[PDB]
Image (tube, rainbow, N blue to C red):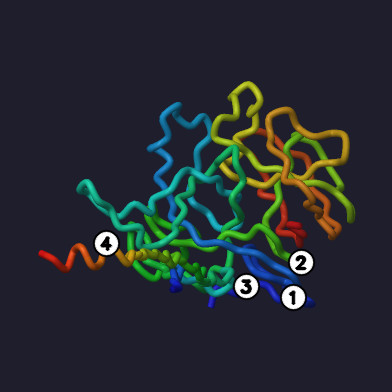
Amino acid sequence: MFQKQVYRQYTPGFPGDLIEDGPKRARPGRIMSLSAVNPAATATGPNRASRAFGYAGDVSALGEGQPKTIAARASEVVIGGANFFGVLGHPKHYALFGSAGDSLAPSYDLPDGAEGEFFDMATGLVVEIFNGAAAALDLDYGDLVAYVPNNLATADDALGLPAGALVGFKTGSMPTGLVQIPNARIVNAISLPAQSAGNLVAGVTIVQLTQ
Amino acid sequence: QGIVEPAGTAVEYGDHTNIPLTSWNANFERRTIVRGELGMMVGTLEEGRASAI
């Protein structure tokens, strides 16, 4: 079903999946609706997997009266935050829930108020990458990555980049409005074609070393 | 005397999530012993005189 082409090899992996085994770190969290942010979000998007997420607050109070029970230690996240919290991954954890039209429809986003696993360290992680300069770019083995915030000004966002997309860049040619992820490398080769607003090429998924 | 004081809290489950841990902290309490004394002394003439009553 749906297979109209035959290729010579299998894809190495899918976005949001671990491609190598080694040291790793992850934490759970609860997704907050993007509309809840007070200064409003200049950049918007869905809660797509393999996108960066930011810390929003603590939701461990679990009570309504004068005394409250601190039952668990939980964290609450938003699609784009100045403070980096992790990258959503491990798609096998969640449920499809179908879509608005009909069930059994391919969906790759999580609803608001749902749980998730976010990665701070990973030897090998397959994520989708983006081009932030609207021009042809070849990354090569050793590079740096960055993610779009919600508070990114429209003047610095001429391209319609999503809320929490990941952008690769060279050592000294970082875009003006992005937030860098320390000690992050591409550790793989990839090439991207020319880019323009409204015709944003989604790039190609690529291996990436978080820490 | 001693105390135990356990500690620990839980988080939501995840396949690749880190593992929370529990611990404890013991303390000790002390009290001090206090001693007292008291004496008496009787003389020969006063003992005989007091026997008159």
**Residue behind mark 4:** B46
Q: How would you rate the neighbour count of disc 1 (Cα within 10 Å): few for under 14, some for 14-19, many for 20 or more?
A: few
**Residue behind mark 3:** A4
Rendering quarter of residue A25: bottom right
User: Mark 4, mark 1: which one is toward the viewer?
Assistant: 4
Q: How would you rate the neighbour count of disc 4 (Cα within 10 Å): few for under 14, some for 14-19, many for 20 or more?
A: few
Residue type pointed to by label 2: Thr
The earlier-in-sequence mark between 3 and 2 is 3
The earlier-in-sequence mark between 1 and 2 is 1
Q: Pointers 1 and 3 in contact (CB under 8 A)? A: no
Q: Pointers 4 and 2 in contact (CB under 8 A)? A: no
Secondary structure of the residue carrying numbered label 4: helix
Give the numbered dot on residue A21.
1
| Residue A194, position as x, y percentages in the image | 78, 40
In whole angstroms, how far apart are the C-alphas of marks 4 and 1? 101 Å
| Residue A31, position as x, y percentages in the image | 44, 52
Secondary structure of the residue carrying numbered label 3: loop
User: Mark 4, mark 3: which one is toward the viewer?
Assistant: 4
Q: Is residue A154 above or below residue A189?
A: above
User: Mark 3, mark 2: which one is toward the viewer?
Assistant: 2
**Residue in the picture at 41% in, 47% down:** A32
Residue type pointed to by label 3: Lys
Q: How would you rate the neighbour count of disc 2 (Cα within 10 Å): few for under 14, some for 14-19, many for 20 or more?
A: some
**Residue in the picture at 50% in, 67% down:** B27
Secondary structure of the residue carrying numbered label 2: strand
